[PDB]
Picture 1 (cartoon, rainbow, N blue to C red):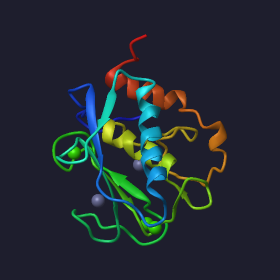
Picture 2 (cartoon, rainbow, N blue to C red; picture 1 turned 90 degrees about the vertical axis):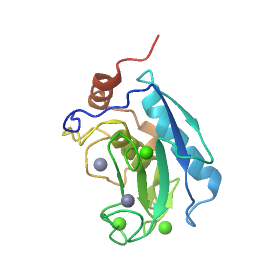
Picture 3 (cartoon, rainbow, N blue to C red; picture 1 turned 30 degrees about the horizontal axis):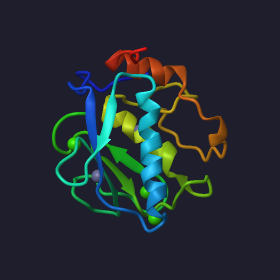
Length: 169
Ligand SMILES: [Ca+2]
Ligand SMILES: [Ca+2]
Ligand SMILES: [Ca+2]
Ligand SMILES: [Zn+2]
Ligand SMILES: [Zn+2]
């Protein structure tokens, strides 16, 4: 596994998130859930907790975008870069942007929103790309299809617990 240089991390245990807008590809209950599941993934292995805001600037802002949007790094059309997130910190930091030129699905018949979000929220929390091929933070998304067997690999667990420790048991 790997962390960003200077090892940025949130100095607080409780973080807030906010879904800025929605995608035409999916009904809203499916977007909320994929984000909530994406967060449980990290909660289960650390003392971090998350709550939702509907106004105000949350720590982790989630949005759907096409081409040029509010930053220097515009998206590239269908395929390839699916989404990108910023390392933890103020403002644009911690935010996750998703390319709406992809077809977000709950299934694996396009780009599964849960798996990619789970991956981006890793970046939002302080994890860079983890070299293990079987790890969630590995930079190559493959249309898995078997979300029925998804388990955070030990490498991801090792890497996120180096940042915030194991959860209180
Ligand atoms: Ca932020
Ligand atoms: Ca793209
Ligand atoms: Ca789309
Ligand atoms: Zn962006
Ligand atoms: Zn990544």
